[PDB]
């Protein structure tokens, strides 16, 4: 089939999709992958053909912009047409389009999936409610006949309530050759990864606090600071630290013993796939959920931003990295992450979805 998968312009949502695109073309089908040009090159590598086409601090009304991409993307509606369209759950436009074309739909859940019995967001978030109705042409995100969730089922909140419409394939990570090549003997020195990723780009005191907390400690520390800070700015970088704007995460996680992260779903599932315990410091609401989920599942510790100190970072790292039972549960969750089936099982469920008709 000619498959069209519609996704928003955000890195977090597109990585899980790429490995699926890679698997699909291996199975034979062809994808038109609508995306913003910035995101176009990553699409190409895994195969498929995607034809190209801000800040989220504001509280409501983001879709219309997604309604603006609906026509822009729908210009190609006519030239090549789908037999199956897959849309990221946030990218509303793909359904509208899809509804109009009455093609089978498959929803992508980058983040937790929800069902009638279980919903996401607090009452305050809940309270906003699709208030203004404009003039053109129900519930914003219900479940499609088949929804692929990029996490093991055991990680899903209220996983008991979830249907056969929901396939929990875990993170979609392929098999690839390491960019990192980080090599010297470890020395048996525990490797800590610190990355807040995209969030907290305005909090340089955090990275300074990490340096103060762990300089000249038993740990070896890799700290991805993004452009939040500039490595040269600091007076003295400790010998046991390695500070970059970016690092190959999957790579370092496979050699790490602890991961201080921001609770992004991609970063969390990668840590789970590598079986690395977590200290989660969340910024956005979804991260707060993931941070809570990590805590309740016993996979690590949830360190709220308002409590992050030199001491709290040390205390957290020490508690986590010293709890062997926590390491076991992390291992058990890693095992679930691999059994989840990945892009392989995701692709298979799409093909078997098409036989049903
Ligand atoms: Na807590």
Image (spheres, rainbow, N blue to C red):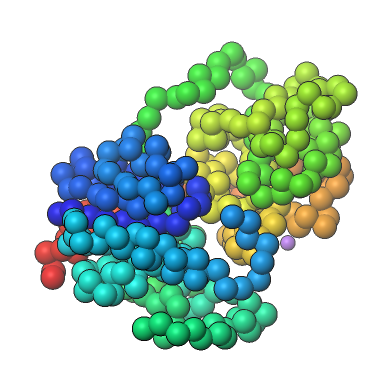
The quarter holding residue 99 reads: bottom left
Q: Which residue is drawn at 40% across and 25% down?
A: 177
- Residue 175, relative to residue 39: is it above or below? above
Q: Residue at x 68, y 55 (%)?
A: 282
Q: Residue at x 22, y 43 (%)?
A: 25
* Left or right relative to 281: residue 150: left
Q: In the rendering, at what x and y percent does residue 41 appear?
A: 39, 37
Residue at the limit of the structure toward the top, as seen here: 184
Q: In the rendering, at what x and y percent does residue 172 appear?
A: 38, 47
Q: Which of 185 and 25 is in front in this view?
A: 25
The quarter holding residue 45 reads: top left
Quadrant for ligand 1?
bottom right
- Residue 237, relative to residue 9: is it above or below? above
Q: In the rendering, at what x and y percent does residue 88 appear?
A: 40, 61
- Locate the N terminus by quadrant: bottom left
Q: Which of 333 and 77 is in front in this view?
A: 77
Q: How many labels does the image show?
A: 0
The quarter holding residue 230 reads: top right
Q: Residue at x 69, y 36 (%)?
A: 227
Determine if residue 295 is in view: no
* Left or right relative to 354: residue 201: right
* Left or right relative to 321: residue 348: left
Q: In the rendering, at what x and y percent does residue 133 appear?
A: 51, 86
């Amino acid at each position: 089939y000619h498959i069209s998968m519609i996704n928003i312009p955000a890195y977090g949502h597109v990585n899980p999709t790429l490995a699926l695109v890679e698997k699909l073309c291996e199975k034979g089908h062809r994808v038109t992958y609508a995306t913003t040009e910035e995101f176009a090159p990553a699409v190409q590598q895994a195969g498929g053909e995607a034809l190209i086409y801000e800040k989220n601090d504001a509280p409501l009304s983001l879709l219309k912009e997604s309604l603006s991409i609906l026509p822009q993307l729908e210009e190609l509606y006519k030239d090549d047409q789908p037999d199956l369209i897959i849309y990221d759950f946030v990218a509303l436009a793909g359904k509208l389009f899809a509804e109009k074309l009455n093609v089978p739909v498959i929803k992508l859940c980058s983040s937790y999936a929800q069902n009638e019995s279980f919903q996401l967001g607090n009452e305050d978030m809940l309270k906003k409610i699709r208030e203004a109705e404009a003039e053109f042409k129900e519930q914003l995100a219900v479940p499609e006949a088949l929804n692929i969730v990029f996490m093991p089922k055991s990680f899903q909140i209220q996983h008991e309530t979830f249907d056969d419409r929901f396939c929990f394939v875990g993170p979609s990570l392929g098999e690839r050759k390491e960019k990192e090549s980080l090599l010297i003997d470890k020395d048996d020195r525990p490797l800590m990864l610190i990355s807040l990723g995209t969030a907290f780009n305005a909090w340089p005191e955090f990275y300074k606090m990490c340096i103060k907390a762990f300089r000249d400690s038993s740990w070896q520390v890799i700290m991805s600071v993004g452009k939040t800070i500039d490595p040269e700015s600091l007076e003295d970088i400790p010998a046991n630290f390695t500070i970059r704007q970016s690092v190959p995460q999957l790579e370092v996680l496979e050699k790490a013993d602890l991961f201080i992260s921001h609770g992004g779903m991609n970063s969390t599932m990668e840590a789970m796939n590598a079986g690395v315990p977590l200290v989660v410091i969340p910024q956005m609401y979804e991260q707060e959920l993931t941070a809570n989920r990590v805590d309740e599942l016993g996979l690590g510790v949830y360190l709220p931003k308002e409590e992050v100190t030199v001491s709290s970072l040390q205390e957290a790292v020490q508690a986590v990295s010293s709890d062997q039972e926590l390491l076991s549960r992390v291992k058990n969750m890693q095992k679930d992450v691999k059994e989840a089936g990945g892009a392989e099982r995701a692709a298979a469920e799409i093909e078997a979805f098409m036989k049903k008709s």
